Image (cartoon, grey):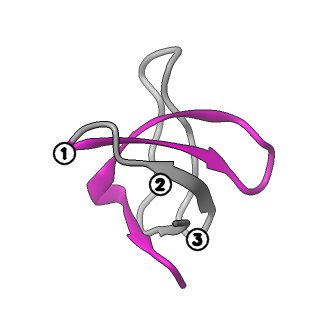
């Protein structure tokens, strides 16, 4: 599925995404309970992000 960011998230590590509220994260992979892997719609970057920063769908 894809999701919409509810809050800005700033990466703190090289393997993380950085995004702002309302950005879409696509091709989500549920690799962990608290951290998911995804791809930004806006630029194709991929990485980990804390799951509570997004909400699936629109």
Quadrant of residue 17 in the image? top right
Report x, y in % for residue 16.
Answer: 49, 28
In this view, the residue in front, 6 or 24, is 24
Residue 22 got which mark?
3
SS state under label 2: loop
Is residue 20 a member of the stretch shown in magenta? no
Are circles 2 and 1 on residues that touch, CB within 8 Å? no
Label 3 and label 2: CA atoms lie apart by 8 Å
Mark 3 or mark 1: name the one nearer the start of the chain.
3
Which residue does the image show at 47% across and 54% down from the upper left? 8
Is residue 42 a member of the stretch shown in magenta? yes
Circle 2 crowding by C-alpha within 10 Å: few under 14, some 14–19, many from 20: some
Residue segment shown in magenta: 33-58
SS state under label 3: loop
Mark 3 or mark 2: name the one nearer the start of the chain.
2
Label 2 and label 1: CA atoms lie apart by 20 Å
Look at the picture and state if 51 lies above or below 31.
Answer: below
Circle 1 crowding by C-alpha within 10 Å: few under 14, some 14–19, many from 20: few
Which residue does the image show at 59% across and 53% down from the upper left? 27
Circle nearer the viewer, 3 or 1: 1
In this view, the residue in front, 43 or 27, is 27
Report x, y in % for residue 40.
Answer: 67, 49
Report x, y in % for residue 2.
Answer: 55, 66
Q: Which residue is mark 1?
A: 33
Which residue does the image show at 61% across and 57% down from the upper left? 26
Residue 8 got which mark?
2
SS state under label 1: loop
Left or right: residue 37 compared with residue 50 = right
Label 3 and label 1: CA atoms lie apart by 22 Å
């Amino acid at each position: 599925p894809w999701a919409t960011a509810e809050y800005d998230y700033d990466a703190a590590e090289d393997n993380e995404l950085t995004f702002v509220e309302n950005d879409k994260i696509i091709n989500i992979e549920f690799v962990d309970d608290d951290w998911w892997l995804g791809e930004l719609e806006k630029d194709g970057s991929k990485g980990l992000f804390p799951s509570n920063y997004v909400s699936l769908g629109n």
